[PDB]
Image (cartoon, coloured by chain):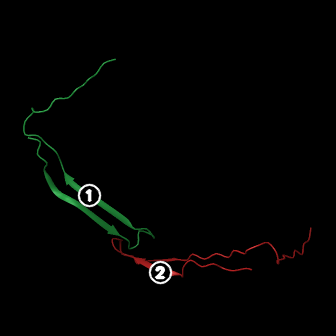
Chain colours: A red, B green
Amino acid sequence: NFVMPRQRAVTVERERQAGKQRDAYYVTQRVNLQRYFANGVVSGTYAAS
Amino acid sequence: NFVMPRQRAVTVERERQAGKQRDAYYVTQRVNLQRYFANGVVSGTYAAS
């Protein structure tokens, strides 16, 4: 348990035409952390009032 | 009469750098339908309450 399924790597695209005097850098990433079943975890917590 | 005048048959364009992560497809055609003289057609009409 605790796998991080990954659709793709990080990518970079760039755009400057038909812009106005300006290179633009765009980056994207699709990643998520999602566990299977609810077992084997704690917080703690650890609290005041 | 009822000639089909045209100056641009169908053009299919394509952009992807970058659109902000979104391709764009553009389709255009330049055409018209026009008659030399005001005669040669009737419409019914076929109308009542």
| Residue A7 relative to residue A4: left or right | left
In the image, what residue occupies the spot 73% across and 74% down? A36
Disc 1/disc 2 C-alpha distance (Å)? 31 Å
The one of A25 and A1 positioned closer to us in this rendering? A1
In the image, what residue occupies the spot 33% across and 71% down? A18
Q: Which residue is mark 1?
A: B28
The one of B31 and A25 positioned closer to us in this rendering? B31
Q: Is residue B29 above or below residue B23?
A: above
Q: Which of pointers 1 and 2 indicates the residue nearer the eye?
A: 1
Q: Is residue B35 above or below residue A3?
A: above
Residue A8 on image: x %, y %: 54, 79
Residue A20 on image: x %, y %: 35, 71
Q: Chain of mark 2?
A: A
Residue placed furthest toward the right: A49
The one of A15 and B16 positioned closer to us in this rendering? B16
Q: Which mark is residue B16?
A: none
In the image, what residue occupies the spot 66% across and 79% down? A4
Q: Which amino acid type corresponds to the residue marked 1 in the rendered image?
A: Thr
Q: Chain of mark 1?
A: B
Residue A7 on image: x %, y %: 56, 77
Mark 1, other Cα within 10 Å: few <14 / some 14–19 / many ≥20: few
Q: Is residue A11 above or below residue B48?
A: below
Element at badge 1?
A: strand
| Residue A38 relative to residue B35: left or right | right
Q: Which mark is residue A12?
A: 2
Q: Which amino acid type corresponds to the residue marked 2 in the rendered image?
A: Val
Q: Quadrant of residue B26?
A: bottom left
Residue B20 on image: x %, y %: 45, 69
